[PDB]
Amino acid sequence: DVAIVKEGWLHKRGEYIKTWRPRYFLLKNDGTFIGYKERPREAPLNNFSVAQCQLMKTERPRPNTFIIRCLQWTTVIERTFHVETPEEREEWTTAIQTVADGLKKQEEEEMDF
Image (cartoon, rainbow, N blue to C red; front, side):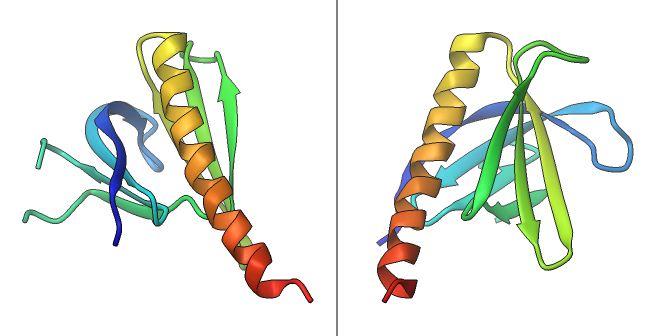
């Protein structure tokens, strides 16, 4: 069964309006990444799988930004996040990458040969 890998507050940049808002996110080891206006039902404001996604780091316009990029059909999806320190960013990007890598291993076990 599915377990929480990491949860906590992130600053998420809006997709239409590129302002930053605080969101409480939970990452689960099936790849679910779900974000709420408040600490958790009430529907989440964000809900997407990190499976088959890529992580990017950037420092502009905000230092300690990371981006999750998912290529899906024709669309590539980007979800942009900020935290207050580079150590905090590494906690999140390591957690997400580890979950994605677990799922990639599983995919390879299914597809190959």
